[PDB]
Length: 214
Ligand SMILES: CC(=O)SCCNC(=O)CCNC(=O)[C@H](O)C(C)(C)COP(=O)(O)OP(=O)(O)OC[C@H]1O[C@@H](n2cnc3c(N)ncnc32)[C@H](O)[C@@H]1OP(=O)(O)O
Image: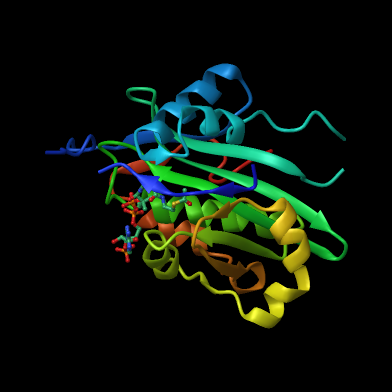
């Protein structure tokens, strides 16, 4: 429900071996078709969340009316093959004066690893959080995920700051067993962060908005 347990799955060639460019486009999951495709990517990376739990987590955005709120899943698609390259699922929270985002799911797909798409998607999330009204991105980080989030600049949330939202967090946020709570404040995100992450993704050009839309 709001508790989980990260169980990761354990010869893999690069699908970007060609000269490029490889055109790619970001998308928001808005159809059952995209929902199925993102769940398929996740299901090859996770043992738990299992198939039912991925279907509970990856959903169409709320049919509501004024700030961003609720669940959103974005993906990056490789246009040559229509394959999903990576995907993130968030929950957007507005609690009293606290406006923040949590990230239950994040993965890069088979054949696309170690190309910079993880850094790129994280950069696109932080840029979206800045542009919408969010103050920070909060991560429930299983022991196996801490080094990754840490490398990308998330830090262990200080206890005094967690205690300010601890009640709302324990009752509303998606908590992985044994996790550490990590955080990046959006005021620390550089304006050129997406530009620099994309520059590092070799042989890729992005068509459409270079970032996440809602
Ligand atoms: C659901 C959750 O929230 S769990 C959080 C993580 N998700 C998962 O574990 C799902 C399965 N794993 C994956 O999908 C991938 O291994 C990911 C998403 C962790 C990383 O995807 P990649 O495509 O390897 O990321 P990318 O190539 O963009 O790497 C970004 C940078 O992080 C580094 N990095 C990648 N994985 C790790 C790791 N596990 N620990 C530390 N650093 C890492 C890379 O070396 C790279 O460094 P650089 O930019 O300084 O050169």
